Image: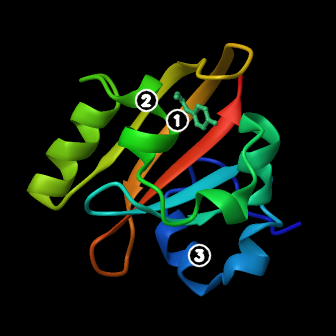
Amino acid sequence: MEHVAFGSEDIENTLAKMDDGQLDGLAFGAIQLDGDGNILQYNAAQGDITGRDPKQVIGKNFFKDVAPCTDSPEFYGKFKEGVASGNLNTMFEYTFDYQMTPTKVKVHMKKALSGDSYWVFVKRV
Ligand SMILES: *C(=O)/C=C\c1ccc(O)cc1
């Protein structure tokens, strides 16, 4: 259980040191996306919430393949804008409802410290 609070101001610095195994000890859902939306990391808390098997979604496109419910200006559009601008820090509520019971969550999207990588953090509300 890695002690990092959701929405922490310096979360990108703290998560810079975690490998896939340490990511699995977070109290919340954590997805790392590349600039095109491909999933690079996907932790255990996130699979708990979504029912996805983390090893099976690495490599897949989040917006096209795994989470089409996020393919809308309200989620993907903010993502695309941040990638385009090279800056991203936003939090909002969303409902996850593809192939699963509709689940309301808090989403925090933030640019990683490292290269062209972007974090998506999720927790139940
Ligand atoms: C909408 O599609 C939100 C996200 C999401 C992620 C994974 C799975 O399996 C369903 C939905």
Judging from the image, the colouring scheme is rainbow
Expressed as whole percent of the image width and height from the top left, the position of residue 51 reads: 78, 38
Residue drawn at x 31%, y 22% is 74
| Residue at mark 3: C-beta within 8 A of ligand 1 | no
Q: CA distance from mark 1 to mark 3?
A: 18 Å
Mark 1 and mark 2 lie on one chain; the one further toward the N terminus is 2
State the residue position of label 2. 68
| Residue at mark 2: C-beta within 8 A of ligand 1 | yes
Kindly state the secondary structure of the residue where label 3 is placed. Answer: helix
Q: Image check: 43 left or right of 64?
A: right
Q: Residue furthest left?
A: 85
Residue type at mark 3 is: Thr
From the viewer's perspective, is the residue at label 1 or at label 3 nearer? Answer: 1
Q: Quarter holding the N terminus?
A: bottom right
Expressed as whole percent of the image width and height from the top left, the position of residue 58 reads: 57, 65
Residue drawn at x 29%, y 80% is 115
Ligand 1: quadrant of the figure = top right
Q: 107 above or below 12?
A: above
Expressed as whole percent of the image width and height from the top left, the position of residue 94 reads: 51, 20
State the residue position of label 1. 107
State the residue position of label 3. 14
Q: CA distance from mark 1 to mark 2?
A: 16 Å
Residue drawn at x 63%, y 26% is 105
- Total label count? 3
Q: CA distance from mark 3 to mark 2?
A: 30 Å
Expressed as whole percent of the image width and height from the top left, the position of residue 40 reads: 50, 69
Residue type at mark 1 is: Val
